[PDB]
Image 1 (cartoon, rainbow, N blue to C red):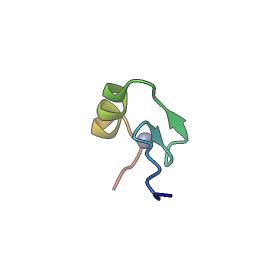
Image 2: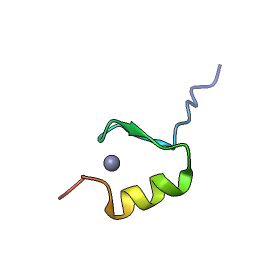
Image 3: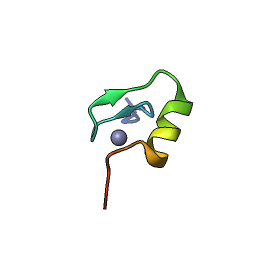
Image 4: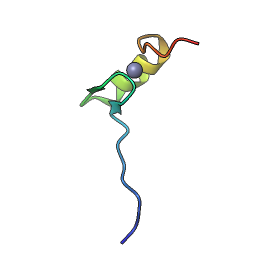
Length: 36
Ligand SMILES: [Zn+2]
């Protein structure tokens, strides 16, 4: 068994998911609340 576990469509820090990858992109861009 490989310990891959993929999930590039869910911002754990925000606690949300996005079916569309484009959403996750635009999210981490300037939509995410991951302020410095
Ligand atoms: Zn986020």
